[PDB]
Amino acid sequence: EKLTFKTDLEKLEREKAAQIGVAIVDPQGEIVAGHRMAQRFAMCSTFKFPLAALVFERIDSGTERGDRKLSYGPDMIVEWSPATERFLASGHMTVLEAAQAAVQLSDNGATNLLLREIGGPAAMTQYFRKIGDSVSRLDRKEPEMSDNTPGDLRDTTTPIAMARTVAKVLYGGALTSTSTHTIERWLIGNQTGDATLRAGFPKDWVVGEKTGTCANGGRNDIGFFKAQERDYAVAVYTTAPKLSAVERDELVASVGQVITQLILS
Amino acid sequence: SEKLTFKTDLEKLEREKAAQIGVAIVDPQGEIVAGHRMAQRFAMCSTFKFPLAALVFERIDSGTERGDRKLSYGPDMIVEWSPATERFLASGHMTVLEAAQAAVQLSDNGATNLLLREIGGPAAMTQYFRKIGDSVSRLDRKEPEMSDNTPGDLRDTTTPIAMARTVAKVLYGGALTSTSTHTIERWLIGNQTGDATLRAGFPKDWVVGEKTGTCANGGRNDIGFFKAQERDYAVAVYTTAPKLSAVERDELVASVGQVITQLILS
Ligand SMILES: *C(=O)[C@@H]([C@@H]1NC(C(=O)O)=C(S[C@@H]2CN[C@H](C(=O)N(C)C)C2)[C@@H]1C)[C@@H](C)O
Ligand SMILES: *C(=O)[C@@H]([C@@H]1NC(C(=O)O)=C(S[C@@H]2CN[C@H](C(=O)N(C)C)C2)[C@@H]1C)[C@@H](C)O
Ligand SMILES: [Mg+2]
Figure (cartoon, rainbow over the protein chains, first blue to last red):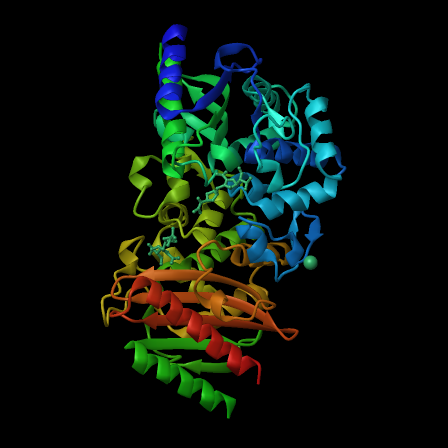
């Protein structure tokens, strides 16, 4: 089963001129399958899911309040900030409004609003370290963190590190029961992932995920799925500079089909 | 004076676009600021989803509903334009508040019908209108058939003045607790479907929240509130333009927005 998994991903890489990093882990973080699993890839927008977990932890701890109003001006509008732009005239979004927009719309301004509050990228890297992730690192805010310069180690993760971080957040007790359920529902309700991994999964699986798109052909999808009453965490990072945007979508869906084959056998 | 210019500019749009435009603007107490065809019936289409959310919030306020209660459903609840309902289908449910937020901010029809199932159907919606002093608005059918917009059909209709006063009652007239009122205000501001309609016609510094509608035979609607020059208003706009394109109808409602702007600013 694992040789077919590797061969099928290698075929996608060959024919699409792509690199595909995949890690699937069980709720304990034990490896189910993987490909280029410790190669570094740009996180791009996928880090917004750990960012929301950070926020949830501070609310859990009484260090933050979900309804606290975060004021801003037009300087905070950057490319792809649809909710931030809608709330601009009102003058604020709450911590939780901003987090939900970052997870479910990949709103960049809302992400940066939260980054300003925690003291910037170093604090997000600090959260990765707190939950046992020594690999993932945030260095810059949006959108420049998505620059994806070849060989740059800034703003990177590995498939296995991020998959284990997903498992830690959802299954390993990083959040309260209530906060864990909330972030799970946010991932299921994500509005940006209809054409990526969940398009390649069976329609009865419960799936939630966070997408990413970066320069130089990056297209990513991380999250969880429940298949045959068993829970998994998954991270998929791909680089395909020669494909169109729609073809990169199709590539991640095709990776979803390869994962399905492995799981169902 | 400025009301006459307001009437004159809207009739200009009506002639040029082969359209009929219903507008009512009221202050927080429901007193008329200005209007056009205010007592004419129009199909509500998706604009009723804002009053539906108010209905749900009132049940939460009164302790007869819980916002986190899970509403289970299967594939037969997915209808045309049910994006959130489709995403949550495998999980098996959508909570009361999840469905209400999808109905308001995405105009999700499946989520709307899920809430209608829980409250008793269209009769319960109409009962809520009557409870808050709206003797005009009526819901008769679920989505999407309630948006048929057959000419002269009285089902699933409101008037601009009736629904502007319903908006003001919900936002300013004490229909909801302070907490629920602020929440529903934020949901309207954060609506994802209105970027090209009324909001596109108001100044960038106005605080605006609204709920759109699109129906058959050329209906395009937008209801909500705006805050301008340190003053609060409720507004309902209903239009019928069967010969316009879909994008042209967005522009029609945005033009109504700047006619409203010209009125308010003098
Ligand atoms: C994050 O990776 C970047 C933003 N995140 C995503 C994404 O998650 O896919 C996008 S693309 C965004 C989502 N769907 C929208 C769309 O295609 N249309 C509405 C037309 C746009 C952003 C690039 C972040 C680094 O900018
Ligand atoms: C209600 O009037 C109908 C639905 N409500 C709306 C609306 O609010 O205008 C639509 S249109 C739907 C929402 N935005 C989508 C879109 O245009 N893009 C994805 C760009 C389409 C529905 C028709 C209800 C009666 O069906
Ligand atoms: Mg500024």
